[PDB]
Amino acid sequence: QSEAPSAITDSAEKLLIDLLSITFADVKEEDLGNKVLENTLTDIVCELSNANPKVRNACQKSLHTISNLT
Image (cartoon, rainbow, N blue to C red):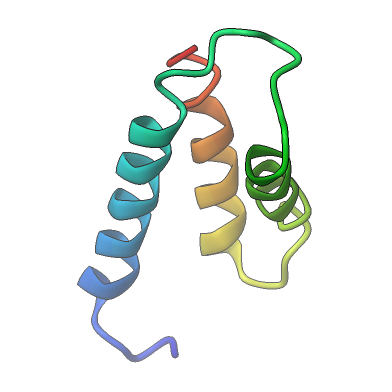
């Protein structure tokens, strides 16, 4: 909710970026997706068209920090 404190969604965004920085560190092949990297990228890029702007900007930032990582 909008009147919840800001550290909830801020800590969630930082945790999502840190988790995607951890689990996408070993992927080097550009066409490497087997079962679960495909689903993680699917749930990220299917949510760029959300109603909430926070999750839109978080999905854009998480797509940017896994294209600069690998």
